Image (tube, coloured by chain):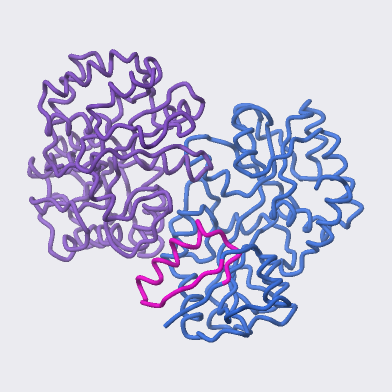
Chain colours: A purple, B blue
């Protein structure tokens, strides 16, 4: 017998936690690593004969799909009472960490106080600072796509399309990863880029003074990016899988998420990092959306039609 | 309940952990942030305006000085049995984390399999590979000076002098901090430099895949840099102070050191980092010196007299 996790989270993040869990509990664990979307597909393709016990996803939207598609078991109050925020109405999965969209910038070139209060205002701001050809983005990156989906949810397709086309008119540089983009900010090739907060945290911990800008509370540019896990209906190892979800919400595992990964924890009693906001301040930043139901479908359509993807 | 800590560890490291300890226990913690050397001066000679409970030091050498001066309470088997290694011969403080001297290099530009087995042979390697002006060091940095002290213990001053003079013949570049030197390694100003392992870890976590060369087991260039904490003879808050010492060895605190700081833990119940060695491998690297008794003053004198410092 082995606990089987299907993970849309990265191996360099998952593996050390799994190894610790194996050592402490004596439970053998096997992990499959794919994208959230590939995991969702495989879980459906495998039907009743899936060996899968848990789905540990990079995104609330993938868990929302798994739930809506009847893959997930309802969770009890013991697990669902643990997180401080983001517990789905479906009560079929548990949020484990949250990450924030932020605006990274070079603080030698831009004063914090002149930065825009809204993402929608970013293209005008970039033209104010003469930044045509001097802004970066990551059009193929999952969280950027999530952010565009939140824009649709808040503002509608037309305003979101308008923004995409305005962004394209800035001649932005596209980077295949967030560290590539942040390196370009450090080098002075671009002066700003929308990214995930923990990439900026990692650069700062390494000694690079990269600016971390938050838009006004509730702005689409601060979208909350919730990760989480659910138990599958197919699970034949429910006690081990419950033990594992418990482990993911423990102070120790949560300290790993904060420290090793740079993400915000969702339980209290975790030591933060001077580069992170207090938890209550972090929770204030995102629009209050149904994160299970972001219109990623419509986001990809717009990104394709506008020439971003 | 209250607790006074004299910390030679940086505020950016100590503060988040102390805040969580306060929140968790209701013990009000007061911290003095200073250097290990300034704290020693206070504990042996200069005095305090109020009694301190704990010396949380950056270095085993400073705790060893405090011990030699008789300023630390003896600890016994109940506290000292938790750490896996590095319990001091004096048994007057508890080891909390370990860091390793390593050789940072740019793996795009340097072939790992060609790097020397001993720090002593670095100047020859560098001269042969035509790397004059392309080696960096941090002459003013505490851990560099510790490594030089390890050299004096292992080799004597005459051998250490030769090495220092052979180094100087490479026209090495001097950097005010480890991040500055690692940035120069990334940028291409130099190709390698002796540093502490966690600086390389932080660079790798940010996406800059700098190399971490370890010398052969026992080599002076792999010196173990142990951090730790001792109870002072002046301690008025003995209950809170012993509770904190226990806390520093707890799974959550140890996870914080691995994650937030990048150091090696000294307990087994912790999730590591794919950029760290397994624990036993890290334990093999350093020579087996009495870390409480390194000739730090001789190292300082020698660095000043060879004009390195």
Q: Residue at x 18, y 44 (%)?
A: A50
Q: Residue furthest right?
A: B158
Depicted B121 relative to depicted B109: above or below? below
Foreground pick, A227 / A221: A221
A202 on left or right of B39? left
- The answer to which of A248 and B185 lies nearer the viewer is B185
Image side of residue B132 versus residue B271, left or right = right
Residue B302: give x, y in percent of width and height.
Answer: 86, 53
Question: Would residue A233 be found to the left or right of residue B108 on screen?
Answer: left
- Span highlighted in magenta in the image: B6-32
Q: Which image quadrant for residue A254?
A: bottom left
Image position of A78 (left or right of B45): left
A193 and A99: which is toward the camera? A193
**Residue A27 visible in the picture:** yes
Q: Is residue B208 magenta?
A: no
x then y, percent, for residue A21: 36, 59
């Amino acid at each position: 017998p082995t606990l089987t996790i299907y993970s849309g989270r990265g191996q360099s993040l998952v593996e050390p936690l799994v190894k610790q869990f194996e050592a402490e509990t004596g439970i053998r664990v096997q992990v499959r690593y794919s994208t959230d979307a590939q995991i969702l597909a495989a879980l459906q393709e495998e039907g009743s004969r899936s060996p899968a016990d848990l789905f540990w996803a990079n995104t609330a939207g993938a868990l929302g799909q798994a739930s809506a598609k009847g893959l997930l078991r309802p969770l009890g109050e013991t697990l669902l009472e643990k997180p401080i925020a983001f517990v789905p109405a479906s009560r079929t999965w548990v949020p484990v960490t949250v990450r924030l969209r932020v605006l990274a910038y070079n603080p030698d070139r831009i004063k914090a106080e002149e930065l825009p209060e809204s993402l929608l205002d970013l293209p005008r701001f970039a033209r104010e600072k003469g930044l045509v050809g001097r802004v970066g983005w990551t059009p193929t990156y999952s969280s950027f796509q999530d952010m565009v989906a939140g824009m649709i949810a808040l503002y509608g397709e037309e305003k979101t399309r308008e923004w995409l086309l305005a962004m394209k008119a800035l001649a932005p540089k596209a980077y295949p990863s967030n560290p590539a983009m942040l390196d370009a900010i450090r080098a002075g090739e671009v002066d700003l880029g929308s990214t995930n907060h923990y990439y900026v945290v990692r650069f700062r911990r390494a000694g690079y003074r990269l600016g971390m800008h938050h838009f006004r509370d509730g702005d689409a540019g601060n979208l909350a990016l919730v990760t989480g896990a659910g138990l599958l209906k197919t699970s034949k190892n429910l006690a081990a899988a419950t033990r594992f979800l418990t482990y993911l919400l423990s102070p120790q595992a949560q300290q790993y998420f904060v420290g090793n990964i740079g993400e915000y924890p969702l339980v209290k009693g975790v030591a933060l990092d001077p580069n992170l906001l207090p938890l209550e301040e972090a929770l204030a930043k995102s629009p209050k959306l149904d994160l299970e139901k972001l219109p990623l479908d419509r986001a990809l359509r717009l990104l394709r039609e506008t020439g971003v993807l």
